[PDB]
Picture 1 (tube, rainbow, N blue to C red):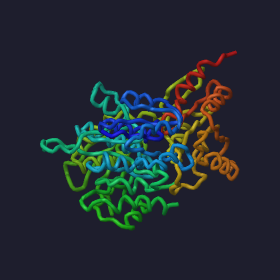
Picture 2: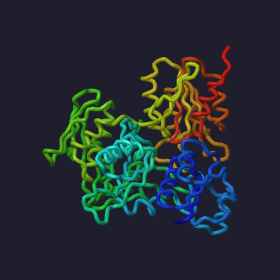
Picture 3: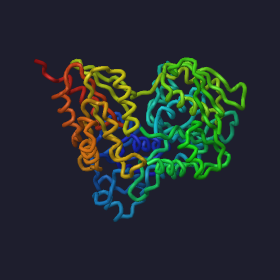
Length: 480
């Protein structure tokens, strides 16, 4: 039971590590510039102690280990103190790899689009099927049933799950579902998650652009390590993915196809909108069933098919997996309406990178018709760039009427420049500004938004508690 201190602990990824660490029995403290919900509340309930600011005093007394988030850099007092005093430190992904993943059969999902859709669907299938899989993913499914076990499992976007059972062979457990992405390296360990994580089942969800080689290289770093007895699951007929494998692969492939190096798994559409389809696996005549769900779109069918195949790889029948997805209620923080104040609609969405922001805003425009649309975005900060041109963030917000981006004071990372440079170079990407205070963003909205408008808040986490702070402010405006 070590004492672990986490720098940046209120953010989704690092907070997830804190929660997993507590579940392991560790004592967990942390620092963040702000303490904000929903993660603060989850941390507090788990018995984590959070302190405000990045202060040397937070590392007194000395913890056994410091887990360092991506925003930390040299020149910061707490970091210079850490290095001078010789405290032990590690990155988030290395900590997770050593403390949780090493002992599990890890299922990692990579892709340019829809990674969290696929991981939420997969984690749902596993738990529906009675497999007590751990996970650290980008969101959670909505749980509409009165099943209090599924309610508790999906209370957080992290869950430890159980270890492979040493005595009872009837139990199928010891798994961990995770997203492979370009985030959460640290200043002293620039290895990506594609290098850190060692999945035995890997999904390559897709590989497309709304630097191909940079993305293929990163995917390759994960593919090239999978054991010979593992499985790679990906869509068929996708040259960008076939070329990824061609760099070096030692593991059997299952290829997936949605029909309306040939495929092993097929989803045949019954309803053109993707709300109903049959799933079949070529090597098992019984491995066929129907999905009849409240989701739609070809991307969601593709996501379902790779999730079903991955679950089949670890024992879930096609029948059970398809029953699970037929019961899938959707995903929290996917254009989720959280307020309607003075006729201003407020939505919450987990999009935090260009392809996700694009998809969310496409959906928002289809939904909201002619309403004036405000995008309020905290993109997920990162010291590294992967495949996406600098202009990608600004381009992704083209469909909004107004966009307010957030870059935090003291942890600036070049956002204002990438946006401002993009809007000069391509005026068609419209009206966008980068602000340095959540208070200024809220004031801007309260000041300029009017009855009929819609606001879409986008962040991988709590965005310094902007959600309730905005709803409160909007409800306090004195009408004329």
